[PDB]
Image (tube, rainbow, N blue to C red):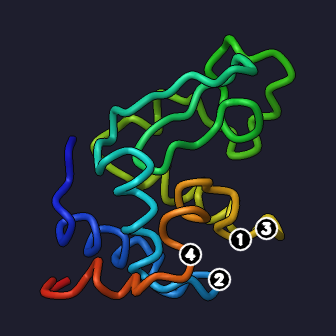
Amino acid sequence: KVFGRCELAAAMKRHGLDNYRGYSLGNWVCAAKFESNFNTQATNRNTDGSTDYGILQINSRWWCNDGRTPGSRNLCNIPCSALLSSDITASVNCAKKIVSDGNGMNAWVAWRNRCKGTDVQAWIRGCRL
């Protein structure tokens, strides 16, 4: 499913991402926009052989298992296909683990290069939530 900005902001809030680990909602929404264009089915293959899955583009080398990434650690103990679902629960739940990593949202290159230090509040403005 392809989410709307406000549609996604509310689903993330409801799933407990607003200010999770100190990152306000606009950060999570900004990240998803640049990571998957709000599309839950997005996948992107990496040079090292791993693939990124879903709305938050979670990587198959550490977080999920896609059965084709040797040295996969599957930290969120879930098959990667579970992250492509129209229900963002598994992505949100695994994302909470990644952000708790000790590296924050820097784990998402699109967040680091395009969201970090911008008025991220602009991403939820006008949304009911």
Mark 3 is surrounded, within 10 Å at the Cα level, by few (under 14), some (14 to 19) or many (20 or more) other residues, namely few
Mark 4 is surrounded, within 10 Å at the Cα level, by few (under 14), some (14 to 19) or many (20 or more) other residues, namely some
Earlier sequence position, callout 3 versus callout 2: 2
| Residue that carries the numbered disc 3 in the rendered image | 103
Residue 116 is tagged as: 4
Q: Nearer the viewer, residue 61 or 27?
A: 27
Earlier sequence position, callout 1 versus callout 4: 1
| Residue that carries the numbered disc 1 in the rendered image | 104
SS state under label 4 = loop
Mark 2 is surrounded, within 10 Å at the Cα level, by few (under 14), some (14 to 19) or many (20 or more) other residues, namely few
Earlier sequence position, callout 4 versus callout 2: 2
Give me the C-alpha separation between circle 4 and circle 2.
Answer: 15 Å
Asked if disc 3 and disc 2 are in contact, CB closer than 8 Å, the reply is: no
Which amino acid type corresponds to the residue marked 4 in the rendered image?
A: Lys
Asked if disc 1 and disc 3 are in contact, CB closer than 8 Å, the reply is: yes
Give me the C-alpha separation between circle 2 and circle 1.
Answer: 8 Å
Residue in view at x 71 percent, y 71 percent = 104
SS state under label 2 = loop
Asked if disc 2 and disc 1 are in contact, CB closer than 8 Å, the reply is: yes
* Whole-percent x, y for residue 101 in the image: 79, 64
SS state under label 1 = helix
* Whole-percent x, y for residue 86 in the image: 27, 43
